[PDB]
Length: 601
Ligand SMILES: CC(=O)N[C@@H]1[C@@H](O)[C@H](O)[C@@H](CO)O[C@@H]1O
Image (tube, rainbow, N blue to C red; front, side, top):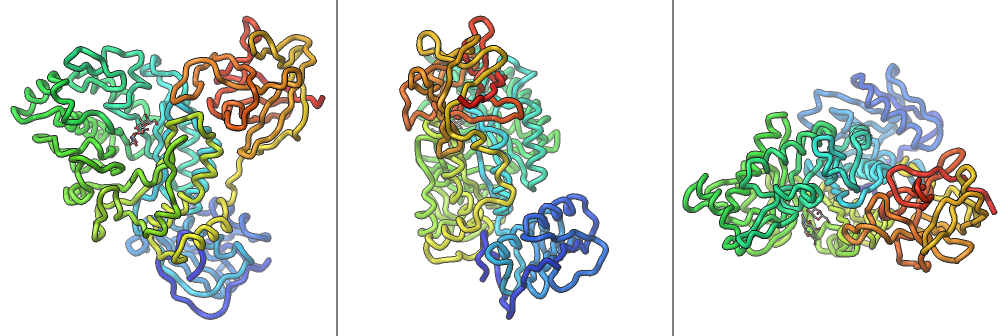
């Protein structure tokens, strides 16, 4: 079988080889489809040489034929294709997506030497949800980084991107504090996902983990028997609580424009806490009788969100850990997808969830990457023959129609411990592994070493890189705006100082940033002031400063964002830019930027 990733579901080999010559063309000989044609024009360019795209002439030996035939939808589904490698290559699919995935395989087949052994496959995914999740909460993850991830996902036939993030709110401006995405930024991500055949699954977590929204709304916070508020927890016994959350959901769904909504619902309450929340107890018993629990009120709240989003043709998803068999009266609505990440205690088992007839996704903790914490051990998973049947706590003995797939999940828990560019490096093999496990073809090799070699040979998606990480040669520069230059000032501060001749040693790092070191003091430009979340300096307005250079301080790493006349400096961790403070000229971090001209010194 061919060395492609994910591997083909089957392969019937033949004799001979297809070879790409400068005579080859790309032939679209099915239905007219502008998306398929645009994708095909990119594909034609991603091959060596100069292939033209046509949709009027018959195919010929040596051509790559892309045949979109909607009548094949029953056989091939929305994402499958039929590949023939002969004297010509033929990809037959029912949809633009299926043709695209076929062309991902073709690129890999021709990568090494423009030749491919002959044969054929019907290649259809074993699972319908093949995912990566990124938690872009507290911190901000750049849109350029997301575009690169989407290209890489698409190149490996992954089709689902979960994003937990705050949208800068017009509905509730008191929640609009960094990190967030603007509505234009969200629409940019939406456009990217559509282009790369990826479904976005946005999340605002509720009714736990709401500290990023409830900080300025103490009236909505859950109180215990002692009267003590839990800042991250919404009081679901208050009607104003559901109204608040569904408002924020509505505002986010308008811009994300996704079919799915993920409301989270992880880490809200456990039964050992029930003596301390008699008001949730009371509210539950009032509604659902003498056996009802706080978990019944929780499940009901989720079902209410379900009804809300279903009214606008959307579908709901949650994490699994709040399903612990204590909802005595109120079952979770069956058309809510449950993403299983955690087992233990009385948490409901995968088998039990699947037996209930709901969609269940495997989002195992084992598939997590956590800044400063656990890293998915792809080698071990490969060596132990991990598949989506292997949930935390339980391995299923057979498949199920309602097991949707799996995803890897990226979390920022110790947010200053690792840059997004370092996470990008770390996720390379996880991404290929979950793509392989969910597409569902046979292993290319018994052991991991062969898989890894193949993955690294293929490398990133064609067109992956979307930035220039090293726009300045390493050296000493003055950084100027008008009459001012960046310079050291009082109390380890840095400012834009009129008529200053100060200069800085800029040196690229291995992870796509620069250190910025004062030629005067020898100290490094850093972000260590202001409010921290998850250990990271995320306050807009916080002053920048100088500190002893450190190889481990990720807050000393700066991204150079380029223009023709000037550049801006973005902190790797905070994702805010160096900005001049008007009152005193101090360099501070904000969502704007001061444009600086680099002048060799
Ligand atoms: C769904 C999920 O992973 N929930 C939480 C996550 O919110 C948090 O970052 C982590 C801290 O260790 O605990 C759990 O993993």
